[PDB]
Image (cartoon, rainbow over all chains, first blue to last red; front, side):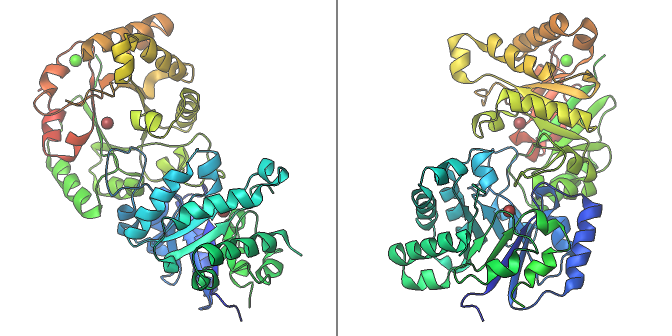
Length: 240
Length: 238
Ligand SMILES: [Br-]
Ligand SMILES: [Br-]
Ligand SMILES: [Ca+2]
């Protein structure tokens, strides 16, 4: 049915311990996820290896962040090389919490994108405007600036997914996704615009997934709180 | 007297194969009596390292955040660290302060949370070259220490690490001043019992002389912690 393969990422954020995450993983393994959804789970960094060992190999594992060189004097960071060594195949970059709580600049995010892709990871590249920005009427400026930094660091979009986070919060998600796809068409290529998944972040739940997934430019979801809950399986099945 | 303390900060280095080999060499080494050894692996390898290291060596995380769970993509909490079997966290490392912009206020909040959650804390302080050359080392490190101390109720599980950021090639002079700070601003008892470890460059060839200084209680070792000479550093008092 869709033009781009449906993509569902679950961002566990800074939540869970071995016991509770083991239970979450058991539930996902028992769901037998459909072949037509690409599912990725992003555990806290201390649990990437633990989670990859237990999770169904059909579900991919992402790190929630990484740094921009293979090794070095960066206490508290991890590199793409470590992510791959733990069996993870994706990284989430530019998440709103890294930008707005931890002050990660666009320049730094672009450098991380380039390094992660060179190292062979997939990247879930996050963008989004804050409340003050939406109220000031500059949604497009903000998300187009963020997207261009990402694009300037992407040579091959096959392993990139763009995630729009409505940090400020007919469907408003659809309006933004259509504009982002138009940006890709005009500034990268029609082929990249037509093939790149643009997934919706923020507060996706079992109650909103079917309506949002029916929007023509919404290709999936980056799921926060609901990724810890049984309803994540219903989100995976939003197109079934 | 104060138990000699040797921490190895692996920073953002190593993979399972190379860290497994490093751990084998540490497991085979004889750790002297009255010496507390701690290794701080990259965050992706805290659990791995704890599983492979002999219990004689403790594991530290290289950083943590200031609440137990929450919407902090990319962070880990003290509860997760303890769940992986680690018993320490390094907080305030110069790279966190200067590359990643962590404020004194944030570091203090992390210290309080990690202690409340049952971890030991290696709390790092230190001046940059421009501060050393301006003559303000003491002012800088005293203020950093004050923010830490305002967040420490019980010093039993705290170790203070002095890292002159520029010392990549004195220590005793600063350690003596920091101990005097503890004496005047906390208590004589805390000053006498708290380990103050040196986190500037330490190698096998410099460790014995540093360890003999009266106010140096051990080391937070950087690059040498990845190398065989870390075992010589563990033996710096022998
Ligand atoms: Br999220
Ligand atoms: Br260090
Ligand atoms: Ca001494």
